[PDB]
Image (cartoon, coloured by chain):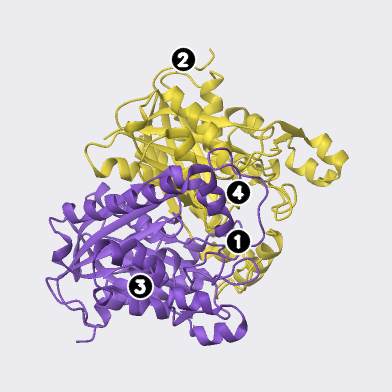
Chain colours: A yellow, B purple
Amino acid sequence: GDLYVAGCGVWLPPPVTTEQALAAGHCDRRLASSTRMLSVAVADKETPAEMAALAAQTALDRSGVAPAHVDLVLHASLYFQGHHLWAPSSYVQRVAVGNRCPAMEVRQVSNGGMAALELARAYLLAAPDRVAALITTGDRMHPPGFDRWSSDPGTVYADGGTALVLSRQGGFARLRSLVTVSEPVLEGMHRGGHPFGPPSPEEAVDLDAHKRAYVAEAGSSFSVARVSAGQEEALTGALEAAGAGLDDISRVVLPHMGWRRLSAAYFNKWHIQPERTTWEFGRRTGHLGGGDPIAGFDHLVGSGRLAPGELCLLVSVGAGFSWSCAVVELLERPSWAAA
Amino acid sequence: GDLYVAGCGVWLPPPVTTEQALAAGHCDRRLASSTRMLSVAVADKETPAEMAALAAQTALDRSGVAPAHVDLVLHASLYFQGHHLWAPSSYVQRVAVGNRCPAMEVRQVSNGGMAALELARAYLLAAPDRVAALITTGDRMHPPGFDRWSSDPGTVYADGGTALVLSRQGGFARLRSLVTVSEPVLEGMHRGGHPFGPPSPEEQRAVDLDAHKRAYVAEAGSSFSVARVSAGQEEALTGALEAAGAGLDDISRVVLPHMGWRRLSAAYFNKWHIQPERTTWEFGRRTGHLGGGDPIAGFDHLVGSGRLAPGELCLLVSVGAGFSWSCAVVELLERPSWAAA
């Protein structure tokens, strides 16, 4: 039961450069300097479902899969979708797909995309006649409730949508492994209340205060170690299930986090070069919720930086914590891609 | 094979009566009479994940399933969970399960519980060695962003958590069928913006689904709207009954959404010609609408009160904005130890 990537796509609103953010006062020099971000996709009027649906159309057109063959629609996101008690995956389905399979949201903060992928894989493998699934991500990190530069310092949040078509029948790439790891002991790091008691009443987004409170309670040593372990389990699990080692991977699709965070988590830990990653693409794009590994994959394939036969390693992590890693093999250059 | 319900449970905060709501100005007489609500579970200090995990503990303890046998944790909800960029499913996993399987949110508004049930079923069937899945729901519908009595007149929203443990190995009830129906043409009914255009960027600080439904109806047509909603509901019912090899007459108990009397009568009583006494009406009208968790809480109620007997069929009915519908037919195999006679 091999699964394939039949299509993928993004819809990214126009970039706002770091220089502009600095001049506009959204950003300070220290943070610009430590993150080393160059630009971030910023929407004007487009809403999360709208961007997701636009990406889905592109992904569906490319995959050439018929709507009737789309057996599941899964929309992932990490911030407010615009309207309470409303179904944004039903919008995506209405606009991008035009069919009547089940459509629902899946959330796992920044690991949302990979999480939806897990459920999509399972859904496709659970009944013998199922063909394809659509996974979308979409977010809009605007005031009042979100500061894309300072709400989660070290990561700069982007507006935009992404989409992937997963399929049992065929496609341009083969999903060789997909592994997900959970360390729920860390859930309290991203919320108010006692880290090992119940949450406080509701809250605008500010993560740094909660992280410091968590670390003060659980210890710096414990926190760093549990975080390191989870990351390592995801990486190792994915490589092993794909019969590869890190030396067998041509490109690593990393989260679109700032330089300081990617150095501590990946570059100085795994000892890989940034030229082997999507660092340059991510630092011009910003963090797209749970859609980074989709945006990053789509970039590598679309620009021809990934070659037939080559293995690609997707790396994703979300508050919780949850980590996912996948090894993807490119089978052929798709027609929408350059050489 | 087929799946089983191995355990279930709820955590409901203390009830606020309609009398109280009338006295507080939260409710008018007209609304009190049309919905015929008696009370609604209202949380005081408790947040949605907390109540979800409390319900999960009850369900897991009842199921007797080891945490290591819980291969998936799915948390559903339809409203704000209390903290942005934080993982309520991880909170649930941490507090209630203590294991390390994937934990994630599934949302499909008021059909969230059943939506999660679908994904959990798929997940368990996908690999031969997977045993159990935990599905929780939780929500806290407080001012000033929400009015549990009038944001969506006709339904009164509750605070509370529900949980259900699904298993491939066994349990006290068998899942005979589960069917989900989608009608995305209706998605516009619950947001601003043009019903067939993009969503409005303008967010609305106070939820008012009534204004949204009118704008939708005015554009799409009333005749069209009622007809699609009816068709969807009818497909879900007939689908689940057929898939289980049963008709409506074979059903002993029906678990309906905890909507107001007027709505239940239009959608089910005057439509399916089923008796309210055979449904969870009395339980729901004291509980209120728990978002996606109504089918779980209703089922939990029936089983725990002894109102369902071995070999009897139970029909679960659920619907959410979108629209999405799910029905399921569950067969009680044995009275569990925690139940009454």
Q: Amino acid at mark 4?
A: Gly
The residue that mark 3 highlights is: B297
Foreground mark, 4 or 3, reads: 4
Residue B225, above or below A55: below
Q: Are marks 4 and 1 in contact (CB under 8 Å)?
A: no
Alpha carbon of mark 1 to alpha carbon of mark 2: how far? 46 Å
Q: Residue furthest top?
A: A339
Residue under numbered circle 4: B192
Q: Amino acid at mark 1?
A: Val
Q: Is disc 1 on the same chain as disc 3?
A: yes
Tell me the element at label 4. Answer: loop
- Give x and y (percent) for residue A62: 45, 23
Callouts 4 and 3 in the same chain: yes
**Tag 3 secondary structure:** helix
Separation (CA) of disc 3 from disc 2: 51 Å
- The label number, if any, that marks residue A335 in the structure image: 2
Q: Which badge, 4 or 3, comes first in the chain's sequence?
A: 4
- Name the subunit of mark 1: B
